Amino acid sequence: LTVDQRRWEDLKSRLKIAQPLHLPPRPDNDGFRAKMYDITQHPFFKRTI
Amino acid sequence: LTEEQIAEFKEAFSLFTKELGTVMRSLGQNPTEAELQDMINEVDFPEFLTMMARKMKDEIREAFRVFDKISAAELRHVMTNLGEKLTDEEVDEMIREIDGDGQVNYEEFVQMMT
Amino acid sequence: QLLSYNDLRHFQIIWNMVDDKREGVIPTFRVKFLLRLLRGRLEVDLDKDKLLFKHMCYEMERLHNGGDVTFHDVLSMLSYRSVDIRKSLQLEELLAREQLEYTIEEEVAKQTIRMWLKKCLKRIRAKQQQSCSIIHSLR
Amino acid sequence: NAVLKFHTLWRFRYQVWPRMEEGAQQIFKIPPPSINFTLPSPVLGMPSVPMFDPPWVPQCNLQQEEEKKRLGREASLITAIPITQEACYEPPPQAVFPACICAAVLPIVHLMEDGEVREDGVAVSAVAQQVLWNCLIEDPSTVLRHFLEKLTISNRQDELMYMLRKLLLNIGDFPAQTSHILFNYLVGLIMYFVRTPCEWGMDAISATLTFLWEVVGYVEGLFFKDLKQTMKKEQCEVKLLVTASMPGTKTLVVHGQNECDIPTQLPVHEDTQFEALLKECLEFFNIPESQSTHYFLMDKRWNLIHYNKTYVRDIYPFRRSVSPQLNLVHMHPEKGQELIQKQV
């Protein structure tokens, strides 16, 4: 196999492994949970954690 | 946003009962202001899409990019295989309906569309 | 030259934005609402790629006849169409893919023609049925 | 001299336009060559066989090399190719060979059987054969198009097949290109007659088939798979291959004596003959048993009178959206029997 073919096969395998993101949508009925989701997903929060 | 609804509605229900008319007017349409609530009764991006896509559902480029071949027999068999419950009665008329060269130009066919 | 993780992450975000639930399947008519919302390296230009976008929509409508389509199907489709298949596929798979795309293209072309066919058939059926009513009167 | 003059006209046909006014194609009009045939796509056979080691193409353990080269060079028929046309360099030219000169081919074919010898030892048949061979190897299309197109406009298939057979037997061969184009054209004609209704369509098909098997012996790369796929794509494999499977029409529609009268939509199974269909037609149309031997089912479009004991699914293999239209026509039993005999 050429390198391009090998990479294609690897990509196929990866996409097989890939699954839908688990993160649910941000609730919007109540501002409480809204701000909670907004602050939680902020990248700096993860970095500091 | 854009002329086509998909990239419009991420903004039209994120950037903004009456103000979304300023978006609707981009289509050239000015429906009754109360109907702006009728759409907002869908509150939801995919529901808005499923409503208005079929509202908008309710030209020559395509013709020139489908003429990828058309002899008389070619048209005859292509259309008869493609077509619905025709009875091979119209097709004598289609082969006979302007130059009579055995060739069709789809620009004139689109003209005779309506 | 290949679909990366940034592209996959963006596609996942768009999927979770067009798929309201976490069911992992969408009715095929929703498929376009994926392809045209997809941005960045995977974006398609509606003002230059109309044929290609229509081809993709019909392909993901044929994969299961009017069926609901999974995340993996659309992801495989974008993968195939985002690579120079002649370089990155085996011979038999390259032939299969190219014959599939050929079939899709001619199928969608005549699927466009069928609408004109339907309209003209309507007109001529109306005319001939009124002529058959006349002949019935002649009875 | 007539034969030689024909040859000269042939060899000078590309040098007419240059001799007269510049841009005279617009001011002088020659009607285009009418061609109603759509040859099978892809082309059925190999258009030509390459020379093994052409001394006029510039590109290109030893002793083996020479041996192989010699053996391959012996196998190749240098006299079957237009040497000077292949050997010319490739860097448009239009040919003016009107349809009334192509008719001269047939008299030349006849002359190929003329044994008379001139006082210089030249025989008419030898020069005729040389001229025809050179034309056929150079351009079969220009020399056969007239006949092929003429057949469409008139019912003279028998004459065409007789001429082609005489040509084959007198020349004793068809070089690969001649047979390639001939076969493709014949198949195209067959499919054309299959599609377009015609009074002498099936007769033409029969005539063509009576001779096709002689041409098929000279096609070099004709394989079963390719033929099958091409014919299937053209939807006319039944008329060519006995090993063709096609689900026949599920139902049939038959019209009565009067015009626009209520037809009948009858079913068609895998083992139904026209006899039961005709019996149902008689029962539906209230025809007395005394006058029951004068009515026959016939296809006006294709001009076919149906035999009682021939299966329906065989005559209408196509399972399209449109059911075949038949007619219950009344006529004298003797004439109906004669027509049935002829068609069978």
Image (cartoon, rainbow, N blue to C red):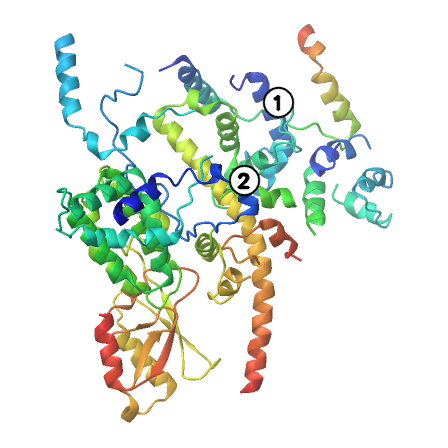
Residue D81 x, y percent position in the rendering: 25, 33
Q: Residue at x 13, y 21 (%)?
A: D71
**Lateral position of residue C108 relative to residue A5, left or right:** right
The mark closer to the camera, 1 or 2, is 2
**Dot 1 falls on which chain?**
C
Q: State the quadrant of the C terminus of chain D.
A: bottom left
Tell which of C63 and D1 is nearer to you. Answer: D1
Residue D61 appears anywhere in the view = no
Query: Of the numbered discs in the image, which one, if any, rests on residue D328?
Result: none
**Dot 2 falls on which chain?**
D
Residue D308 x, y percent position in the rendering: 24, 76
Residue D144 x, y percent position in the rendering: 31, 49
Residue that numbered label 2 is attached to: D21
Residue C16 x, y percent position in the rendering: 62, 29
Q: Looking at the picture, does residue A38 appear above or below residue C50? A: above
The quarter of the picture where residue D106 lies is: bottom left
Query: Total of numbered circles in the picture?
Result: 2
Please, what is the three-letter code of the amino acid marked with disc 1?
A: His
Query: Of the numbered discs in the image, which one, if any, rests on residue C10?
Result: 1
Tell which of D235 and D18 is nearer to you. Answer: D18
What is the distance, in whole Å, between disc 1 and disc 2 at their CAs? 68 Å
**Lateral position of residue D218 relative to residue A21, left or right:** left
Please, what is the three-letter code of the amino acid marked with disc 2?
A: Glu
